[PDB]
Length: 394
Ligand code: HEM
Ligand SMILES: Clc1ccccc1C(c1ccccc1)(c1ccccc1)n1ccnc1
Ligand SMILES: Clc1ccccc1C(c1ccccc1)(c1ccccc1)n1ccnc1
Image (tube, rainbow, N blue to C red):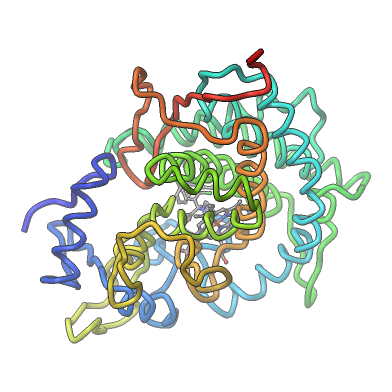
C-alpha cells in the first residue's frame, strides 16, 4: 500500500511489478500518481494522446514546455516540430556514422588492458565523441562538452525528491545550453553540413527553429546518447555475462547481434517508466482516474508481462523483435527519434567487444558497480575482465 521500490535492487523491483500486474494493475500511490503495469494497458495509454498528454507543465502555474523539446508536446504541435528536427537529424545522417563509431570504438578498446571499467573506457567517451562530431564541434571543445554531460549523468545517481535537484541541473545545463546556442548563432553566420547547420537551416511548412530551440534539441541529443549508451551497453554485457553461451554464438555469427540488442532492451530497458498527464476524467482497465493527474507507464513491467511475451523472464534473443514494437523506445507518435542511433551505436560497440575480446565478464573483485537509484535501470560503472585479448603472448 506504501512505497514504490527503488531501481537499484532490480530483483525486488521486478518481483513487486509482478505482484502488481497480478493484483493491482492500475495503482494510485501516496502522491496521487497512477501506475499502469500491464502491457495492454500501457499500450492503451501511450496510444491515446488526447487523454494522456505528454505535457506535464500544463498543471503547474507558470511553467511551460522547453522550446525545441518534442517529448513535452502533443499533436498537432508535436508532429510539426518533429518534422522540422527530423529533416535535419535524418536516417541517412545516423547510418553514415557507422564507420566513425566503429573507428572510435576500436581505438578506445585497443588501449584498454584486460581489467577496466567498460563505462569509463567506452560507454561514456564514445557517445560524447560521436554527438560532438555530429554537431560539428571543434575537437578542442569536446572535453568540456563531455564534462557537462557527465555531470548531468552523475546527478541521476541522486534522489529525485532532493529539493536541490532542479538547481543542480540548472548549474550545468545553463552553461551547456549557452554554449550550444552560441554554436547555433555561428552556423547561422556561416552554415556547413554539420547537424547544427542543418538545424538552423531546416524549415518544414514555414516552421523554422530559433537558436534556443536548436540548442535545446542538440542538448537532448547529447544527454540521450550519453546516458543511454552508458546504461544499455552495461546492460548488454551484464545480461550476456548471465547467459555466456551467447558470446560464442555472436562470435561465430555477428549477424546475431541486433536480436541480442533487442532482447536486452526488452529484458533490461534503460527507462523502466514514462509519464503522462490525464486531460480529462478517464479509465484504464475499468479503473477510474480523474482529470489532471500523472500516470506512470511501466515499460519494465509491460516487457515482463506474460500476456505480451511468452516465458517473459527468459533471456531469449530468438524471440520476434525489432522495429516499432520495441516498447523500450516507447510506442506511438513519441517513439524514440534516436532509436536508429541507439541500435547502431550499441551494435557496433558489441561487435567491437567481441572482435577484440571474444567476451567480457563483470569483475567480481570490484564493486565500483553502483546502480542508478532512480529514473534509469542500470549502473554508472561496469568493472569488467577480458580473459582473452590480442595482448596475451600465449
Ligand atoms: C537505448 C537507447 C534509448 C532508449 C532506451 C530511449 C528511450 C526513449 C523513450 C522510451 C522515448 C519515449 C518517451 C515518451 O514517450 O515520452 C524516447 C524519446 C526520445 N528519444 Fe530516446 N532512447 C534511446 C536513445 C536515444 C538516442 C541515441 C537519442 C538521440 C537523438 C534519443 C532521442 C530521443 C528524442 C529526441 C525523444 C523524443 C521523441 C518524441 O517526443 O517524439 N534517444 N526515447
Ligand atoms: Cl533527467 C531528464 C528527464 C526528462 C526530461 C529532461 C531531463 C533533463 C536531465 C536532467 C539531468 C540529467 C539528465 C537529464 C534533460 C534531458 C535532456 C537534455 C537536457 C536535460 N532535464 C532535467 C531538467 N531539465 C532537463
Ligand atoms: Cl535525454 C534523457 C535524459 C535523462 C532521462 C530521460 C531522457 C529522455 C527521456 C524522456 C522521457 C522519457 C524517457 C527518456 C529525453 C529527455 C528529454 C528530451 C529528449 C529525451 N531520453 C533519453 C533518450 N531518449 C529519451
